[PDB]
């Protein structure tokens, strides 16, 4: 049908920053994670490399996607698809050419796909403050992130869902460890420490004559993968403005809903969650200045000059949001 043809055409931009992910979500019947993951797995020849049966991949992807909440405005299957595709583009950076193995590539992409699964639309701090069952289970540390991992891995056990069935025991152990290390690193409470270590690597950077990064041990390799997926997670402000604005509307909706729950419970309303006392534009400029730009400028230095266009877009968007403040 016409819908299928237009979807296929939009998916031709899968290797580009600024993919029309919302349009893909609409055209696919709200299956952006399934179609984008499938497209990327075919593009990178991952099904053949890891002997993943196509039916198994689609079954797992659809099940995983079903565990993202359709009533959560930001932390849903569209965000997951976006982080997956963003990681996919970052992995193709010329400075990282042939740096990571196929298993490491698989781990980064899989981690991106499951990284927010079953997100309830409220923060770790909210879960801790409300004495939730999740915070009790996880002892207040990386509560959501531990849960996303547990669900992502548990779903592999469903009927015809083990996409890693033909990996060796060693490969399965290695992939699991890498995925856990990556998703736990998406917890924002770990941002400052991750950035500090990324800055240290940039200062002690070792490269070939062409500018390709030389990473030998696991500690350095996983650190780059952790920061890569963290950058992908925090990539909305670096995308074309039309996309960024849509992501902002979505996170503000989610935040305001959390603030409504806090207000009625007599709790202090979390930053950016009070719909009656919000400054959306000022908050975006602040988030770029204090979190997103420091991170992306450091990533840009690591892969210089491959991320210049991304950094340029970030700065363009910061300038535009600032202009909306009288
Ligand atoms: C698109 C704008 O996103 C944010 O402001 C934001 C913050 C702050 N925390 N998480 C997100 C996604
Ligand atoms: Mg998360
Ligand atoms: Zn996320």
Image (tube, rainbow, N blue to C red):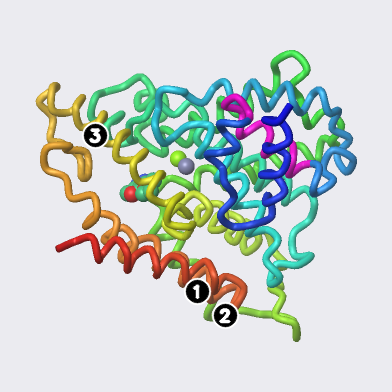
Q: What label sits on residue 228 in the rendered view?
A: none
Report how far apart the C-alphas of labels 2 and 3 lie in the structure: 43 Å
Residue at image position (61%, 28%) is 31
Q: Which residue is mark 3?
A: 256
The magenta span reads 28-41
Residue at image position (42%, 51%) is 244
Report how far apart the C-alphas of labels 1 and 2 lie in the structure: 6 Å
Point out residue 179 in the picture as x, y percentages from the top left corner.
Answer: 63, 42
Point out residue 239 in the picture as x, y percentages from the top left corner.
Answer: 49, 57
Assess whether mark 3 and mark 2 are in contact (beta carbons under 8 angstroms): no
Q: What label sits on residue 200 in the rendered view?
A: 1
Q: Is residue 39 magenta?
A: yes
Assess whether mark 2 and mark 1 are in contact (beta carbons under 8 angstroms): yes
Residue at image position (26%, 60%) is 286
Q: Residues within 10 Å of mark 3 (few under 14, many from 20)?
A: many
Disc nearer the start of the sequence (3/1): 1
Q: Residues within 10 Å of mark 1 (few under 14, many from 20)?
A: few
Q: Which residue is mark 2?
A: 204
Judge: label 2 CB < 8 Å from ligand 3. no
> Secondary structure under badge 1?
helix
In this view, the residue farthest toward the front is 2
């Amino acid at each position: 049908t016409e819908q299928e043809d237009v979807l296929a055409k939009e998916l031709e931009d899968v290797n580009k920053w600024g993919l029309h992910v919302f349009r893909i979500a609409e055209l696919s019947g709200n299956r952006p994670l399934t179609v984008i993951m499938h497209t990327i797995f075919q593009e990178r020849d991952l099904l053949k490399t890891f002997k993943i049966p196509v039916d198994t991949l689609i079954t797992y992807l659809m099940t995983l996607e079903d565990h993202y909440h359709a009533d959560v405005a930001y932390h849903n299957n569209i965000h997951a698809a976006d982080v997956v595709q963003s990681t996919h583009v970052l992995l193709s950076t010329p400075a990282l050419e042939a740096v990571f193995t196929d298993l490491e590539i698989l781990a980064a992409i899989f981690a991106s796909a499951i990284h927010d699964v079953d997100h309830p639309g409220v923060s770790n701090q909210f879960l801790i403050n409300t004495n939730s069952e999740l915070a009790l289970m996880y002892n207040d540390s990386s509560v959501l992130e531990n849960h996303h991992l547990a669900v992502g891995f548990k779903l592999l056990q469903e009927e015809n869902c083990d996409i890693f069935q033909n990996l060796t025991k060693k490969q399965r152990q290695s992939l699991r460890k890498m995925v856990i290390d990556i998703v736990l690193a998406t917890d924002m409470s770990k941002h400052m420490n991750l950035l500090a270590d990324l800055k240290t690597m940039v200062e002690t950077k070792k490269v070939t004559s062409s500018g390709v990064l030389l990473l030998d041990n696991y500690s350095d390799r996983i650190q780059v993968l952790q920061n890569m997926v963290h950058c992908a997670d925090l990539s909305n402000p670096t995308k074309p403005l039309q996309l960024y604005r849509q992501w902002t509307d979505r996170i503000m909706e989610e935040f305001f809903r959390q603030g409504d729950r806090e207000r009625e419970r007599g709790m202090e309303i979390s930053p950016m969650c009070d719909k009656h006392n919000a400054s959306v534009e000022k908050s975006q400029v602040g988030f770029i200045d204090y979190i997103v730009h420091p991170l992306w400028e450091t990533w840009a230095d690591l892969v210089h000059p491959d991320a210049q266009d991304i950094l340029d877009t970030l700065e363009d968007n910061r300038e535009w949001y600032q202009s909306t403040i009288p």
